Image (cartoon, rainbow over all chains, first blue to last red; front, top):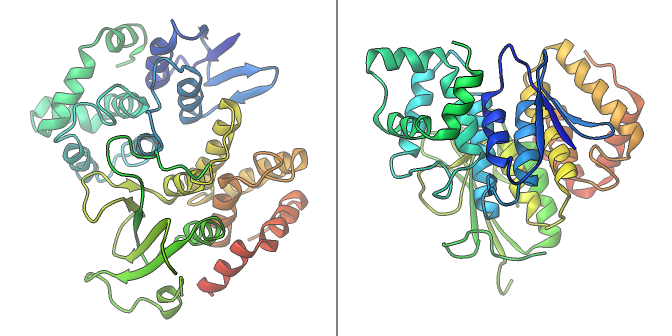
Length: 168
Length: 204
């Protein structure tokens, strides 16, 4: 059917979170490997995490991980690039974190009051970022992100994937 | 399509406001704007923000009846990355010309199955994440990929022009050149089009 080969070295937590949220809805298997590959048909594949996240959310209709309207669709894209660039970075973390903090000031979830790709990719990156944790040791982390991060980290799915996959 | 069901609780789309840096003009957006005009009645206006001085003349005149479907305001402003918002003020603007491009093109309503929609997205991602700031080794790799796919199809994502074509083409223009022939052909395919054509002229 639909198979995903992950890189068991630096696991794409975000994608695996995604797989877990679409399992009942879609039949998907995960295999160990040295790289990330989503096998869809005979020879159509996706290699970069953001393409895999988009295909999964597009196919898992029940899950509603890609929003409900063009606006939320575009917001979710914004957070995909945000996580793949500003957050996938050592420099200007502080500028980046503050930006995220401002956005979460009045939100519970990043987009549309329910879980979405945006929530997965940002959280996954935010976990695997050293600066975030250092802030965590220090207790210097911004208030909103801490709540949002904490809220997600406490959910069953976020702990199943964490337990099985998190290198640290 | 042409529908206006775009924002679920808020009113239907009317005015789009874009902030862009003039040291870094967004050719994709200029091109897309021209494209929208063919299919929509647009009110276009350029502002310059307080924080900017001496915006070049070409940049100022880059847009120069009874009622409008869409309003398009470009504000030249000192921003690190391009932004989009739907009201005079907002909290989380959509950043990044790639994301702004997907949204605008979508207003045309040309739907795609999950695989094609994701491939279209993937190309847009390559232009932004690899081709835009990439090393020559990276640039060469991209060219290679396009060439392979442009021998399968006349357009990057299939038989029709997508936002994949617009974005990657525009990025190409603003960045040592060895160019495959499918790519060199596909360039021509694009330049033939009026919208692509005029916008290129504005950057001079």
